[PDB]
């Protein structure tokens, strides 16, 4: 009855958005049902290993707040949680499946397989090792029993392949995709065990899902064409298969096709949760985290790529998502990635942070730009700016007038927006430079003279900013102070 799910990334590079979503739905499904979330490292393909990938995965899950219950770091009752460390388990089950009619030995070399691939290509076809071709290749079905015996005495390298049944209809049932049927004649005699005795992912994963008592396999639709094989492997072993749920690939923001790093490089959004430096080129892809996406906003955005809670509430915490996540409500249709939505989520979460919660990152941005201000002023600037910001860095980049005087003045704004009025304003501001009192003084000057408030406010804004932007003028004057306010006014008068 206890739900057990597993996230099974390979240590072959960084997590993509699809992988983050799979991990999230694993976590939400396990926690919603009071079950267990397992991390199993799929490191049997030694030649695709990227140093630091396991550490990357753990750091990303920790950043988002989805720590596995069982993992290499935490241990657990079914350790080892790295597949490279489970060879004795795999050997036991390799011996078992070789007693069935579902597996056979194959001796074909890479050159021999390249040769038949070229023969098919010349006919405009694609080679598949399957029922149709296995009898003309070199394996324990096609070769005389005496030749196989001879080859094994000679220590000839061999793989173990699954023996696809002849003309059998497999009826599959997926939680996301529903019921469908597949004829085994469309499927291949996939390799189960490599030359060195280690399983391929197909065989390792069904062995370990069985051993680790996994109840629900949640994964991407890239695995869906292999589902029939996996169900047949459980049958071959005399085992009950878990339930499956196949998530449709995330779609491109615009046009046909699936989301790829090409879309991130062409549209300007990140593709990995954390910084990843490619070892081949030394170039670093900046992650969501380092680009300033708040983890609560990031994971809220990822959750909604194909799941819509019944209450139509878009902003939800991890605890709220745990309470209402229903795997049967995840859409079969692909969901388009939206950079707009990701930025909107970030803005929504940023606006609700306290000024104090924003201050550490804001001070980091200031330091990177060689700017220093008191914490008192920094908190006030954050309060004045955060409602319009999408990222904390925007509070500086769009508020440079808090720290730097204008050197020029926009001509269009200069034309739209006299020195006597400004001189008279300079005399009146010599008081308690508070925004509420400054505005009261400006209204007193406007009422004393014969002009509407904009006749004072607009040229004043131009003087302080160089263009017509920024927060309310009396707030800006309070932030930069009396001396700097008058300095900028006199500079604008002289210009
Ligand atoms: Mg369903």
Image (spheres, helix red, strand yellow):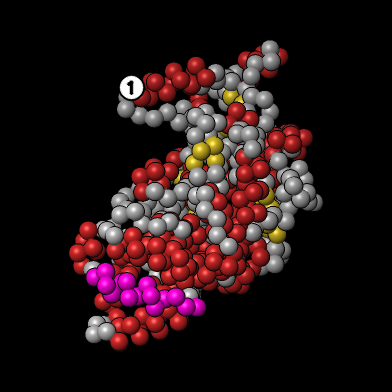
Front-most of residues 394 and 144:
394
The residue nearer to you, when weighing 8 against 321, is 321
> Quarter of the image holding residue 142?
top right
| Relative height, residue 276 to residue 342 (above, below) | above
* Residue 7 locus on image (x, y percent): 62, 51
SS at badge 1: helix
Camera-side residue of 191 and 432: 432
At x 73%, y 52%, the residue is 70
Q: Is residue 99 visible?
A: no
Q: Which secondary structure class fits the magenta region best?
A: helix
Hey, which quadrant is residue 64 in on the image? bottom right
Horizontal arrangement in the rendering, residue 280 relative to residue 8 (left or right):
left
In the image, 166 versus 413, the foreground residue is 413
Farthest right residue in view: 77
Q: Residue at x 30, y 54 (%)?
A: 408
Q: Position of residue 46 (x, y in %)?
A: 63, 30
The residue located at (48%, 21%) in the rendering is 113
Q: What segment is highlighted magenta in the picture?
A: 418-432
Would residue 252 be visible to someone looking at this image?
Answer: yes
Residue 174 covered by magenta stretch = no
Q: Is residue 410 above or below residue 117?
A: below
Left or right of 146: which side holds 447? left
- Please report the residue visible at 40 percent of the width from the left and 84 percent of the height from the top: 440
Instruction: Tell me the residue that label 1 is attached to.
Output: 122
Can you say whether 2 is above or below 192 in the image? below
Quadrant where the N terminus lies?
Answer: bottom right
Dot 1 surroundings within 10 Å: few (below 14), some, or many (20 or more)? few
Position of residue 483 measured from the top left corner of the image (x, y, whole percent): 45, 65
Give the position of the C terminus as an image quadrant: bottom left
Is the residue 289 above or below the residue 103 in the image? below
Identify the image quadrant of residue 296. bottom right
* The residue carrying mark 1 has its beta carbon less than 8 Å from ligand 1: no
């Amino acid at each position: 009855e206890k739900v057990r799910v597993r996230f099974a990334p390979s240590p072959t590079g960084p997590l993509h958005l699809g992988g983050v979503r799979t991990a999230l739905y694993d976590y939400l499904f396990a926690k919603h049902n009071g079950g267990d979330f397992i991390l199993r490292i799929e490191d049997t393909d030694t030649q695709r290993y990227v140093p630091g990938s396991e550490e990357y995965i753990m750091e990303a899950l920790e950043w988002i707040g989805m720590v596995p219950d069982e993992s290499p770091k935490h241990g657990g009752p079914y350790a080892p949680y790295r597949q490279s460390e489970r060879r004795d388990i795999y050997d036991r089950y390799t011996e078992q499946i070789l007693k069935t009619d579902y597996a056979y030995l194959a001796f074909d070399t890479p050159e021999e397989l390249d040769q038949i691939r070229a023969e098919f290509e010349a006919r405009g076809d694609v080679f598949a090792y399957n029922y149709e071709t296995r009898n003309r290749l070199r394996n324990s079905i096609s070769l005389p029993e005496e030749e196989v015996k001879k080859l094994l005495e000679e220590k000839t390298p061999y793989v173990i392949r699954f023996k696809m049944p002849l003309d059998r209809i497999i009826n599959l049932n997926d939680i996301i995709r529903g019921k469908f049927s597949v004829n085994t004649n469309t499927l291949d005699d996939k390799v189960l065990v490599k030359n060195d005795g280690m399983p391929t992912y197909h065989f390792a994963n069904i062995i370990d899902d069985h051993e680790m008592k996994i109840t629900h396999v949640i994964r991407g639709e890239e695995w869906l064409p292999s589902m029939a094989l996996h169900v047949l492997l459980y049958e071959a072993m005399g085992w009950d298969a878990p339930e499956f749920a196949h998530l449709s690939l995330i779609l491109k923001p615009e046009g046909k096709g699936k989301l790829s790093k090409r879309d991130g490089d062409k549209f300007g959004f990140p593709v990995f949760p954390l910084n990843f430096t490619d070892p081949a080129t030394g170039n670093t892809s900046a992650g969501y985290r380092e680009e300033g996406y708040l983890p609560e906003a990031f994971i809220n955005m990822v959750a909604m790529l194909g799941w819509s809670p019944a209450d139509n509430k878009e902003i939800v915490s991890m605890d709220e998502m745990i309470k209402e996540f229903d795997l049967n409500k995840v859409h079969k249709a692909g969901a388009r990635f939206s950079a707009e939505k990701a930025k909107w989520f970030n803005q929504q979460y940023l606006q609700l942070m306290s000024n104090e919660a924003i201050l550490p990152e804001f001070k980091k941005v200031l330091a990177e730009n060689n700017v220093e201000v008191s914490d008192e002023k920094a908190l006030k600037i954050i309060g004045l700016m955060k409602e319009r910001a999408t990222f904390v860095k925007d509070i500086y980049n769009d508020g440079k007038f808090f720290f730097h005087a204008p050197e020029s003045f926009d001509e269009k704004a200069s034309k739209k927006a006299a020195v006597l009025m400004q001189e008279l304003t300079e005399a009146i501001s010599s008081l308690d430079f508070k925004a509420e009192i400054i505005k009261e003084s400006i209204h007193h000057l406007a009422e004393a003279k014969g002009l509407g408030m904009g006749k004072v406010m607009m040229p004043l804004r131009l003087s302080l900013v160089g263009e017509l932007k920024g927060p309310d003028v009396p707030d800006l004057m309070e932030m930069i102070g009396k001396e700097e306010t008058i300095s900028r006014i006199n500079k604008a008068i002289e210009t």
